[PDB]
Image (cartoon, rainbow, N blue to C red):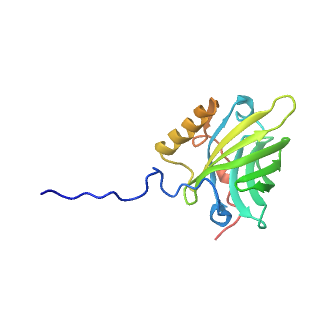
Amino acid sequence: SGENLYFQGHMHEEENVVRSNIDISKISGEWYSILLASDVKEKIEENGSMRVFVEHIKALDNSSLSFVFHTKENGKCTEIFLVADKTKDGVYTVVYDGYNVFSIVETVYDEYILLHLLNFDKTRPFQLVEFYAREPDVSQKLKEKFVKYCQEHGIVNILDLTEVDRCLQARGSEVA
């Protein structure tokens, strides 16, 4: 006798984690910048060009993606509008502080996006890893996931943005 037990689920571990065949409509909407990492720490510390705080992602056509960010310039939150062009599933290019490529590494559409960017500056090229979430903070488990990804890629300058000025106060342009 005893309770018969039965395997349930799939063999791989993660639930609803999307790594390819990205559905753009479901990654659209409101996002918050949570974590930022780089191999060049100056790019993400205060005054760094890549210290940008995402606001919204929108599908533009069957290819391109609109990204709206805030960044700090001359003491103020300023809104910056970017259009990223698709080169293949999950991969885009965009011009900002030079020429960039970036990849949607992994996403849970209603929770988070992990993005890995390369910038091709001739003198000081760099990599950026970003973690966006559907809320302004995330679980410790997800922060550890991000940190492990960074470590696996040799990226050791890792900032948690959730207790510093991310220009949240600048997101109130539109009312219900």
Location of the C terminus (image quadrant) = bottom right
**Where 55 sits versus 101, above or below?**
below
Q: Is residue 12 left or right of residue 39?
A: left
What residue is shown at x 65% (from left), y 44% (from top)? Answer: 130
- Which percent across, then down, holds residue 42? 74, 30
What residue is shown at x 64% (from left), y 30% (from top)? Answer: 154
What residue is shown at x 54% (from left), y 36% (from top)? Answer: 148
- Which percent across, then down, holds residue 76? 76, 45
- Which percent across, then down, holds residue 128? 70, 39
- Which percent across, then down, holds residue 120? 83, 37
Q: Is residue 9 left or right of residue 19?
A: left
Location of the N terminus (image quadrant) = bottom left
What residue is shown at x 58% (from left), y 43% (from top)? Answer: 162
Q: Can residue 76 be seen by looking at this rendering?
A: no
Asked which quadrant contains residue 101, the reply is top right
Q: Can residue 128 be seen by looking at this rendering?
A: yes
- Of residues 5 and 17, the one nearer the viewer is 5
Name, please, the residue furthest toward the front: 1
Asked which quadrant contains residue 83, the reply is bottom right
- Of residues 106 and 158, the one nearer the viewer is 106
Name, please, the residue furthest toward the left: 1
- Of residues 122 and 172, the one nearer the viewer is 122
Total tally of numbered discs in the picture? 0
- Of residues 1 and 160, the one nearer the viewer is 1
